[PDB]
Image (cartoon, coloured by chain):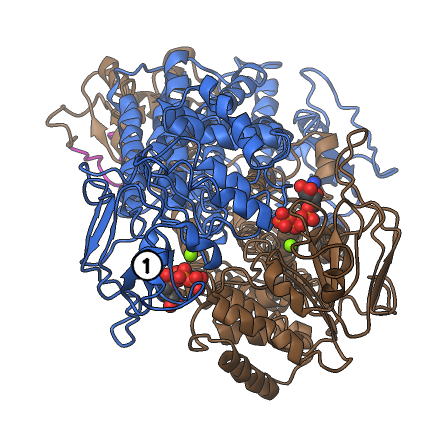
Chain colours: A blue, B brown
Amino acid sequence: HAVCVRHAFKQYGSKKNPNHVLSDLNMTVAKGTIYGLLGASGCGKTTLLSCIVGRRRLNTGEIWVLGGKPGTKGSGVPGKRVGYMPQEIALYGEFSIKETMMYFGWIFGMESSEINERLQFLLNFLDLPSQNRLVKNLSGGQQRRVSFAVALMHDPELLILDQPTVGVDPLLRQSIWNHLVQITKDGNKTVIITTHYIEEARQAHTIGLMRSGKLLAEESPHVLLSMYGCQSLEWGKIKALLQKNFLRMWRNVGVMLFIFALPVMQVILFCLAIGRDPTGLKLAIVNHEKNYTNQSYQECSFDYGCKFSYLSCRYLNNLRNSTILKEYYPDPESAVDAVKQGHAWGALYFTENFTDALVARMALGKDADPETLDQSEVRVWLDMSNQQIGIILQRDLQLSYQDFAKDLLGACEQNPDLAEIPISFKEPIYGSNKPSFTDFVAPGVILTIVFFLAVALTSSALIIERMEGLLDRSWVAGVTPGEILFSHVVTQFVVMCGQTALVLIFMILVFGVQCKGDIGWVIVLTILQGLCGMCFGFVISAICELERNAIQLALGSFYPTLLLSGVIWPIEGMPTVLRYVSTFLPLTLATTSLRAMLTRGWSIAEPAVYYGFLATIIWIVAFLTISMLVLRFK
Amino acid sequence: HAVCVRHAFKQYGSKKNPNHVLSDLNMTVAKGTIYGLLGASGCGKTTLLSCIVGRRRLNTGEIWVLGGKPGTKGSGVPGKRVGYMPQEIALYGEFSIKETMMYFGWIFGMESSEINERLQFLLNFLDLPSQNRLVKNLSGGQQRRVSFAVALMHDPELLILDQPTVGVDPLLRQSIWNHLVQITKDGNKTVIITTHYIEEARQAHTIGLMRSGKLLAEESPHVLLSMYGCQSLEWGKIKALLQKNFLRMWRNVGVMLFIFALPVMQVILFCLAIGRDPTGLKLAIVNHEKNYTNQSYQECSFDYGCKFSYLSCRYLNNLRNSTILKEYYPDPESAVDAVKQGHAWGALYFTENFTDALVARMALGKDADPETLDQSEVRVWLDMSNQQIGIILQRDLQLSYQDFAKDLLGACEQNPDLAEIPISFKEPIYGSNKPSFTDFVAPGVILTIVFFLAVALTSSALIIERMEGLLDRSWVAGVTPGEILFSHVVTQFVVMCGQTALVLIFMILVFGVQCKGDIGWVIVLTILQGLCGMCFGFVISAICELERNAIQLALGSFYPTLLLSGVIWPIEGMPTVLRYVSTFLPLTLATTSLRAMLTRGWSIAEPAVYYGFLATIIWIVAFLTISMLVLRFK
Ligand SMILES: Nc1ncnc2c1ncn2[C@@H]1O[C@H](COP(=O)(O)OP(=O)(O)OP(=O)(O)O)[C@@H](O)[C@H]1O
Ligand SMILES: Nc1ncnc2c1ncn2[C@@H]1O[C@H](COP(=O)(O)OP(=O)(O)OP(=O)(O)O)[C@@H](O)[C@H]1O
Ligand SMILES: [Mg+2]
Ligand SMILES: [Mg+2]
């Protein structure tokens, strides 16, 4: 007995509308007989064959196949001893015949020098073109004959052919039916071929017949006649599914080269845009001591030395000569009317009696009457509608006043240290005295460019299996569903490391970013975050089913992981509850650890550093068990 | 007459290794005869039928069908007068039988009350289940029968069928072949049916035959059997494809509600995390005037009033009671050893004779000597390894010294105004005197949340057509390429406006981003900017065939948008070449216009405002013609 089923009960639909496809289904396939499962279009015929190879659970029946229940250690449904053929052509369209016969070649442990020893024989038996032609340009009949040879070469001992002769001319159909009757001559193989052409089914030995949810009769075709009628009929698996993932990238070279040009482009833009201070902003200076001529011109022939003359046009040219452009107006009421409509960013005003009011405010002290302490002031109106240019504009006018004040003392009377606020900031312990925005955000972006590029790579990898077919007919071949996932991790970790190192080269070597700490541990962490990123793209593909429903889910996680992590604002700005929640995240703790390597210089031994590795290894495992659990569930 | 081909030529293979599928191909279909195109498996049979309906173009030949070549206004190829059944079942599996009959119903201009009668008649004729059962839930023989009732209901005058009776039992295949005879009794319609089931092909009366790229015979069967052998001779279209787009968003309500929760979640996080001043951060204060006890106690009593005693403790409690914690150490060499290992963010130092050296500095004035200069300084070491917290700490110790200085002159007898540098900043013309980082990035993130969400929506739309079929046999039913794209804009612009207004409500009304200029124009710009985003996602789908290149291309074009538009840094730091290029972009000219509406208050009439509308309406047209040119001709 090859297959034997007792008391089979299956049905789809809700309890309010039962279907009742199968009712009893008591049959027995004697070993060595070409069992033929004929029937009527509409009954449960494929749903029985699909219940034999363990594709659908039988819902409280008894099924015994080649030793035991399907999918159990005592039977042989998944393995090299069971042939198969689906109703629809489940073949990958981008493979040549010589490649699709090797993908299934060494899944069943066939030697590479033995597959092609019979590939030519199979191509000669059933007519087929040259073996280098991809199976997408093949006709509709030469695509069925390939599927009949893919799952016949390994010489199984139980064939589950369903509709194998649909779409070929009668000569080829006779040739196909003249083969199942030759290999079965000895008691070694069984066939369960089912077809809808009953005339050709006379060659079988144990023709079955289904009428209503149960087998009607199972007798020889010439015994069926004269009783019911009168006349006529009334390492292998890993290596196999790893040269298919690698071959996929090579098939469309040109877009695979694009993914290697993304990190270099995304890093060049960041270094060339963010951080550099503005250098092309203007001002409206209306100094009322020099006669107003032209628009971009005014005399500045002040006195150079201990003689204090024309102090107004000495504070000018004492500020930055490159980040501020000077423009002159004759009327204070007109300068404010120039910044108002957007022709400048500010407007100064030096009163007519400025030098006298300032030379009498330093020599005289603590006796400054309000009249004297009202004309020595440099009135400035700022267009503070940008909150980032006005901040450096008002940080430059008064910082440049320090040089103006120190120049007075250091040239005439005393040591250039009186004009200093008593608070002295010494030398910073870790950083520099001139912080830059491009250095606070750089360590948090390198860990983010890598994370998102890895997510986009492995975002549809687990979802294209249904796209190309070849999946549900490879489950029968014994492919463990934890074995496809492993081959995706290996086949993409090679290409992820190729662009992770591209970010580091173009951000540390070409563009200067300090690396006071150890360089070995930075690389380990920056690929521990990429691998965590690509494992996050598997919990999306497994959960999602529709292709369009998974693009906008990973893409919808761009901003929330760019704000919740500390990238552009310190993590201490959030309230006391969001800050606590935003610590158990994949990226919020790696930026803090990497910031303590590039700038401070701490090694791994420091407690604040190894938390990044500890809190990113956990997420790798967490994103893997969930992805595996969903895959194993269905 | 009905169809005639003269001197047809077509080859598939590359140059110097041709295929030569067709050589001459001279045939003629009569006025009302059931032409049957039989032949061997491997010749050009489907590629001839697929060249009649205009799916493939001949190389050098003349094809003349229903009075003119395909694609000419005089010929009815892409019309309601041509039936068409493909070799493979090109049906959408998510539609019920009634829905998929109505979708093809009113493409040809069929009244909704007239389709139902034909639907019931066809369901009665060829056995089929209840009309509200999904096609994907049907069997393999009840899915072919549905496809037979779609290419037959509108009553065409030229039926084209290739293998319409495969996978169905003979008792019903005879019924199918018994229908093409009844409807063709008069000289109204023609049938061009190709089958490999030669036994039942004797019912026709113009059987053809192909051997190698040429028609062999075109005679009647019972004449063929007696010639050289004995036996075995070997508004509707828009309405149609718009209740199908509106329907696929109703079968996944679980995820359709998710896309309405992204904008509220992505805006709540931005306003709750970015902008707030850090509040929890410590200091190491080692004041050498009060005895050191505990570690959170310093006995701060400083003789409140005009009397000048314990000035060190007067400066303390004058910084901030909220944003700075205080921790006290007894040794200057130990405070630096606390900030060094991360237990603080700074370390002050008040010398044991601080008050005496400060009460004498404001009296001697210009007569100060270096002995008393370097004894009244609040030495502070700062951990500037964050560059964002150190800035607000360096800007708080000295800004709070202004209060300490004014607390002295304004205490006993003086006017609290001789403590300011001669630079006075007056009142800002447009902004406020206390700029915030959150108010600078908010007008420019709203334009980015909308842009990115629209791209995610309409980026898999044009590549999902090939997934569910219904496109090979939609081009035949007079569906021009223009109106497929148009119906993808109306069906998503409704759902994009539903989340564009969600961003505005949750950013202006609830969280409180000010808007001085005009609320009418902001909504127009933020809607007409999102529409530019959704049109950009169409150019991604038009030029990308494989779906795996859509997630990677769309998600990989995000960082080059934040870093190249002025979202987080004003566009003046880039070099001259990059700054000039960046203005000709969809977003960099629109954030500037929106920033001049919320902050300045300018209306549209200002010339710096309508450039945003003008420079993003162009991109809508530019992204549409390219998305249409590729879609029309490939
Ligand atoms: N896209 C293609 N590119 C190249 N060659 C092709 C392509 N499609 C088909 N061919 C080849 O050109 C010929 C066209 O075959 P065609 O589709 O007409 O066969 P058919 O009569 O439908 O086949 P069958 O009855 O065996 O299913 C065949 O030799 C086929 O191998
Ligand atoms: N996924 C499904 N959900 C519900 N009912 C289904 C499903 N698949 C098939 N059926 C129904 O189960 C019954 C048996 O289908 P089955 O696939 O066994 O038919 P079959 O013998 O292969 O058909 P045929 O030869 O006519 O193509 C049919 O009534 C079919 O409509
Ligand atoms: Mg079947
Ligand atoms: Mg065909």
Which chain does the numbered disc 1 sit on? A
Q: Give the left or right position of residue B478, taking residue A503 as reference.
A: right
Examine the rendered structure and indicate whether residue A39 appears above or below residue A439. Answer: below
Q: Give the left or right position of residue B55, taking residue A624 as reference.
A: right
Q: Nearer the viewer, residue B563 or A20?
A: A20
Q: Main secondary structure of the magenta part?
A: loop
Q: Position of residue B115 (x, y in %)?
A: 59, 83
Q: Position of residue A619 (x, y in %)?
A: 30, 34
Q: Amino acid at mark 1?
A: Val
Asked if the stretch drawn in magenta spans residue B516, the answer is: no
**Which residue is the site of mark 1?**
A223
Please give the name of the residue rendered at 38% of the width and 63% of the height, measured from the top-left corner.
A39
Q: Give the left or right position of residue A560, taking residue B504 as reference.
A: left
Please give the name of the residue rendered at 81% of the width and 45% of the height, measured from the top-left corner.
B10
Asked if the stretch drawn in magenta spans residue B303, the answer is: yes
Please give the name of the residue rendered at 45% of the width and 49% of the height, measured from the top-left corner.
A550
